[PDB]
Image (cartoon, rainbow, N blue to C red):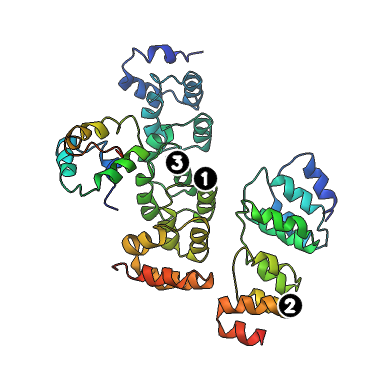
Amino acid sequence: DIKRAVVHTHLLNPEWLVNYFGSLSVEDSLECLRAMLSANIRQNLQICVQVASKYHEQLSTQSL
Amino acid sequence: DIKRAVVHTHLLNPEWLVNYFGSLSVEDSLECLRAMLSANIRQNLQICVQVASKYHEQLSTQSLIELFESFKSFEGLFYFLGSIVNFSQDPDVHFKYIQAACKTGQIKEVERICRESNCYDPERVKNFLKEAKLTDQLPLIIVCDRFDFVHDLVLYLYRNNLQKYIEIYVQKVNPSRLPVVIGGLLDVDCSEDVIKNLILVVRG
Amino acid sequence: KGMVKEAIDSYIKADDPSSYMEVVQAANTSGNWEELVKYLQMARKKARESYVETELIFALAKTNRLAELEEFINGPNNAHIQQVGDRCYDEKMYDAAKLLYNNVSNFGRLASTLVHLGEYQAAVDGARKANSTRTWKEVC
């Protein structure tokens, strides 16, 4: 369970996190996003979309 | 009726008001706060808590927290008692801070106090946990083995569901209590293939 | 004065669950396991405790209200089974630990009571899932 960025998102610099997920996403960021959106608070909301404008260009999955 | 700061709070410098209430509170600021919270607008809301982090140190009255939790206490008590878990030894303050953490998901700030605090009754707590079902159960499996009452926890975990709970418990939390948990699983007679598969997990 | 029967109606009109510990201290002093049932049944809705439910199932088994003793447990009991299950065989009120340990799966203690029950077919079915020395030998 590496996925606990839901709490750090209120404090962590999202810029380098976008690249943390641009890397290490061997079919994995889907599940972390699923966890973040299981706690889709208005604070941690748009960050799910800021990342989203990177991976669509390679895989705009219908699962997403 | 000196109490009309509810309207000035939208305009008045709260700093010197904090000291206006640090003085002149001969059992009086309770009623003024009761009036402010009778009009607990989002604007005049946190100011009720900024004052609150001064008078607790002399009198953390249960009347205060009663009139507090009488309302929603969306995150009011979490911010109030977020600074009072330290410098306290009461069971009720810890328990009700934890219960306030159930109102907005801040369980990550609860798992810390289950370890830090050691001056509370976890029995009423874990009962409430199974009543107010945590929904991401993951402190009870920390505070319970912190207090070694696992003989029924293992059973409750098998009863509701077991996808990660025992696995992530022995993996992350404390692998030192695996075989006792297997003793529990064999008391309840879980499937042996599950045990052969579970033991393959790495240890600490 | 020990008016345990009369100390109850002085709480029915109040619904005050407090001091129930002393109510229990006087309850075992005189078998009255029918009206404590009502006291605890309604005080259930006032103090979500565990003593209430434990002593409740104890009184139920005392008055052998099995049809609903088995139903209360199937809900959110939040009680302490195997502590009154101790009282089942300590007082030897069988056909009770049969139901307490059933949904709790304590294979090894139920069979000690099924010794005195008389059933043997399901006793060994409890033992095969126990596979303990005590269980097997006592069933034998």
Residue C135, which numbered label?
Answer: none
Q: Is residue A40 visible?
A: yes
Asked if marks 3 and 1 touch (Cβ < 8 Å), the reply is: yes
Q: Amino acid at mark 3?
A: Cys
Disc 1 versus disc 2: nearer the observer: 2
Looking at the rendered structure, whether the residues under marks 3 and 1 are on a common chain is answered as yes
Are callouts 1 and 2 both on one chain? no
Residue located 70% across and 52% down the image: C20
- Dot 2 amino acid type: Glu
Query: In this figure, which residue is indicated by the disc labeled 2?
Result: C119
Residue sitting nearer the eye, B196 or C114:
B196
Which amino acid does the dot numbered 1 rest on? Answer: Ala
Marking on residue B132 = 1
Q: CA distance from mark 3 to mark 2?
A: 48 Å
Sequence-first disc among 3 and 1: 3
Where does residue C72 sit, x and y in percent of width and height?
A: 69, 53
- Tell me if mark 1 has few (under 14), some (14-19) or many (20+) residues whose alpha carbon lies within 10 angstroms of its own: few
Name the mark on residue B102. 3
- The residues bearing labels 1 and 2 have C-alpha atoms spaced at a distance of 40 Å
Contact (CB < 8 A) between labels 3 and 2?
no
- Residue C104 location in percent, x, y? 60, 64
Marks 1 and 2 close (CB-CB < 8 Å): no
Q: What's the CA distance linking mark 3 and mark 1?
A: 8 Å
Secondary element type, mark 2: loop
Residue sitting farthest toward the front: A62
Mark 1 belongs to chain: B
